[PDB]
Image (tube, rainbow, N blue to C red; front, side):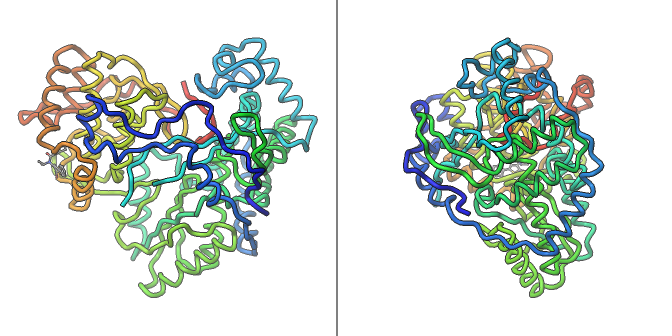
Length: 559
Ligand SMILES: CC(C)N(c1cc(-c2ccccc2)sc1C(=O)O)C(=O)[C@H]1CC[C@H](C)CC1
């Protein structure tokens, strides 16, 4: 069927939309070529629509039915708990889009009688009505990027806050446990950056002659069919569920997950959806399962050898036993034809790679650096263009989410995150003393409220002391960063070193934790550097739950 149908009404914004980076003193320090940074707006929704709208082609086969059964078999071991209204409400982000029924996120978290009564009614309605499509709002997603040698905005579709709270009750436990029980080590979100690097290396070194490739599905969401969504529910249905949880999942599947009407911000009827809605709790899990299923089956159809998959929602990387240059190009092409039949056509054609560092998955790639000792240490890095553009944007304007804080946590070991991001921001934060102001950022979709003064502990727990001494990065890595700093017009190492030394000092100076920041995060700043040792408070932080499952668009907030 058509992934989308449109009435012709427009996808509208519910407020004004900024697209250009503002001329700002504090923002010019970091990035100079401001006219290169932009934000997507609804003004380009139509371009995205034309690209996501089309009629899906899908042909299942024995390999597909076989992998599905293997997956359903493992799903059978799971027992999922029904979440209480209180626990569900406790998972709702503080600034989640309010309900159109007279209450918002604040009330939901407070457990106010009004928000709770409505959630129950929405739940009762789920147990009783198994057909009526549930309404969803469509909006153009606002994302910053850097011009290219632009990008039309991504589309987001989500239901009312009431329903979202119900999803959590019926499915939170399922989407957080199942992926893991079904795909095992292949499930990406169970890994912190370091562990992913480790899995990618151990998987790589386990083959005699490794051959890997990343696989980019063209607008994965619009490629998800009604069959895929029922196949996905068929997997959930294998869990031991509470009766109401089972009705809720059956009803959420027919009334929301497979499709439904689309309403813009103005109340108008925009059209209909018959594919994955990016804004429901099951998006991340559903996609990870679907992508894993099609890839695992496709790998058998293409005669690829020793298929080790790594899946993160729609992002997919494959590492396997090479069979020869020619043979691998043929096997890989066969793989794409298989995925195309299962309705996962390629965006950019996959390319076999024989150098791990040359593989981009989750917009990242593994790379080598050296620590104080001089021993080789692997870390996860990525082209810094987008992280930096976004940092500039987050410096010039005020935003709910702080990607820089999230990028510093996920990429603390990188040359760019420490040199630029840490220096830039800690400098700005001190100059307004807000090192204690907790900020919100995201990790695998989930929203987190993190304190900037706790970054040393976090970096040591997640990446290890080496992250503070990495040096002698790879040739490829410095080229990228160089090329990047040249492009956006960012001041050279010389300038950052100088700014860091100034931040370090004013940090060691003022106090305790802040001094810890200066001593650890900026140890690369001084020549007569202090010998770094394990930070006590580190093993005190509850990093449980940080890397268990993906929640992109799932409206989740961990406290
Ligand atoms: C002087 C040199 C030893 N160096 C270095 C600069 C590179 C750089 C490359 C491209 C653009 C800007 C800087 S790479 C590279 C390295 O260690 O290989 C360093 O000391 C850095 C300084 C920044 C620290 C976050 C990590 C350590």
